[PDB]
Image 1 (cartoon, rainbow, N blue to C red):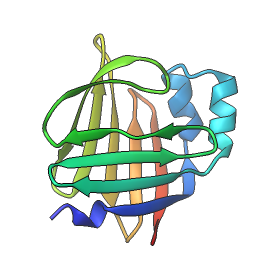
Image 2 (cartoon, helix red, strand yellow; image 1 turned 135 degrees about the vertical axis):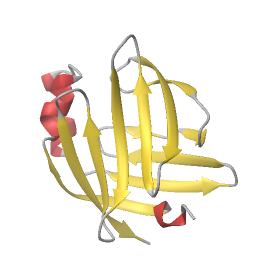
Image 3 (cartoon, rainbow, N blue to C red; image 1 turned 90 degrees about the horizontal axis):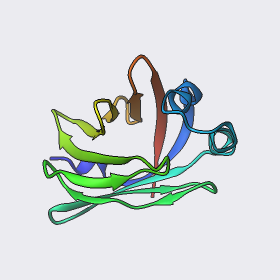
Image 4 (cartoon, rainbow, N blue to C red; image 1 turned 60 degrees about the horizontal axis):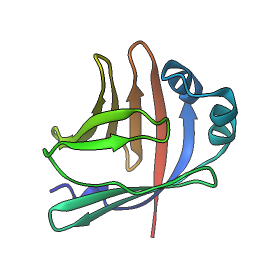
Length: 133
């Protein structure tokens, strides 16, 4: 019923992380500070509205949305994108698009361990979160 996604998550591992930010053309400087960190994600429902908090010593972000309703967003890479978040069968999918090109932040539950796969063209990353109270 989507509620398994709620709570506070903590990074416990990540592989290919760096090739993903190079493929989006993120700067080394930026790439390395933010690659050394282990952030805390929060997933929060509020009626219709959800929210993705990112908490790292590097960046702090909150985005609220309705599922299936598109929105404008600037990332922390500064690209104006068109974004939409959906639920495709217990896979939470965040699509981001701009000028004929795009990227996917897909967040599943495999174990009780939220996996987030990150696909930008021929460039894939996996990042595992564990739950907290």
